[PDB]
Every structure is written in C-alpha cells, then in structure tokens.
Length: 301
Ligand SMILES: Nc1ncnc2c1ncn2[C@@H]1O[C@H](COP(=O)(O)OP(=O)(O)O)[C@@H](O)[C@H]1O
Image (cartoon, helix red, strand yellow):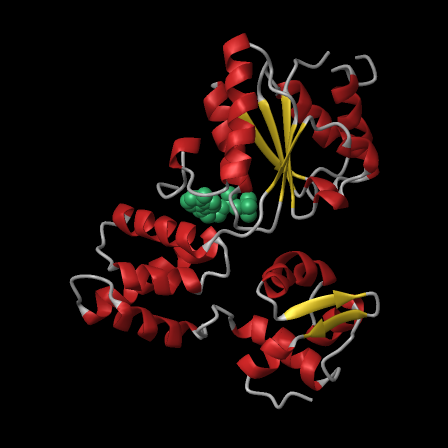
C-alpha cells in the first residue's frame, strides 16, 4: 500500500472534497473533539477508502474497517462498537447494504452512544457508498459531513500516474503519462493498475523509460481502446445496440442479458459510460448515444 496517499497533502485531486474535509478535520483536532460523522459517496476506485484512513491518521485515532454485507447479526455490529475507543473511526464500506438489524443498532449507537442500555465511547462513523441516495433516510441525516467524489480530470490522473511511476522507480515521459490518463476512465485505481501493466511492458522490452510506443503496446495486450473502454464496457454498449436496438432497455433486462448483477452494472460500469457520453438514462431505460455507435464502428440507425 506504498502507493496510497497517507495524508491530504499527498491526495491529488478532489479539491472541493479536501477543502471541506480539511476544514472540519483541522477544527476538530484543534478542539480535541470527536469529528462529526462523514459520508463518502462516489464510484469505486476514487479514493473513498483512502480518505477514511487519512481521517483516522490525522485525528491520530484507530480505524476499524468493515462492510455492510458482512455485518449480518447484531452481535457482529455490537462487538465492533464496543471495541471502539474514544475518537476512533468506524469505517463501513458499502454502508447502504447494512441489514435492518445492524442498521437499527448502528443508528442507535449514534443517537446517544449506547446500545439498548447494557455504553459506547464517542466515535466518528465514516461510511462509504457509491450512491449516497442508496442510504436509508434515517441514517442519511446522521452524517454532518457529506463528501461527493466525481471522476478525476485527465490532468489530475496524469499527475497520479507520474507519482505512481516514481514510487515504482520507473521513468515515464509526459506524453506517455497523458496517454494512460486518457484511458483510465476517470479513475485513480484504474490509472495505477494500467501504469503497473505498462511497467511490465517496459520490463519485457527492456526500455529505459515509458514512452508512447510502450503504452500503445500495453493497451493492445490489455484490450483497452483509445477511450479507455475495456472488453466489458464494449460488451455493454454492443449488447444494447444489437439486442435492444440502441435502447431504451431496462436495468434488470440489460443485466440479465449480460449475466451480471444489476448493481455491478449501475454502480460500477455505467457511471463512466454516462459521464463520457456513451450512454444515457431515460424513464424507459438506458439508451446508447451516437458517439457510442461511431466509436464502435456501427452504422448510425
Ligand atoms: N487521489 C488519489 N491519489 C493517488 N492515488 C489514489 C487517489 N484516490 C485513489 N487512489 C488510489 O487508488 C486505489 C483505489 O482507491 P480506494 O480508496 O480504495 O477507492 P474507493 O474506496 O473509492 O473504491 C488506491 O490504491 C489508492 O491508493
């Protein structure tokens, strides 16, 4: 995890998020008070986990990691709550997936810091979700700080790439870093994994630095096109084009045809497809745009 930022000063991008978090985080440290609960929302790979760890580290408290789909019985949640020390961070990934059982108990420990009277040390709840709207109304109004992360710019991603390459002790030319950033689908996690693969090409071809040639060879091997779309991205668009005539097609129907969970489609793949203008959502369902037809070389109906 030597590539993960350890402080906000090492976190490139998300300027609005950082200025908001920094304000409340520094104020709380200065007062020796427990930070207000924070909600981190946005597509995966954008640094929500990273920020959660940064928060605990800045407050100099312990972070307790867990996720909604794991805490089934109240006992599971109860144990974690009691292990919390004053000022500790309770980080819950996919918090919108907490079953009513543990959700009620969590909400309870937040209203007065005491579960059914049997006592909980004041703590900071930091939840993570792809869509803040997926959270229940009750728990939603519990976070005093809501941070919405959107995709990064190509410039920010390029900077993240150069930073990663330097840490892996490998030289890379600006134009090459730009090329990778343009194909990272607005996501730091994607950009870093791509940089590692390009690093492997640099190793096999025995080059002194990553250039455009090395990047293009890597992308052909990985099957990533000039827009950064991978095999499944294209499969989604092609399926809508061929099986559904460009759409509109419902989320459930599309998911069934692709053999994947609707969630993985709407929370993981569609976000960027919508942002990049390849897909659009209508009341009747998802539809492909003219840009997708042309990018994939299909005659525009
Ligand atoms: N702003 C950033 N600068 C550098 N690396 C980042 C940034 N945001 C995310 N990453 C990197 O990407 C990977 C993914 O991040 P993570 O925090 O797990 O995403 P999320 O929880 O939103 O899915 C991490 O390896 C991390 O170190």
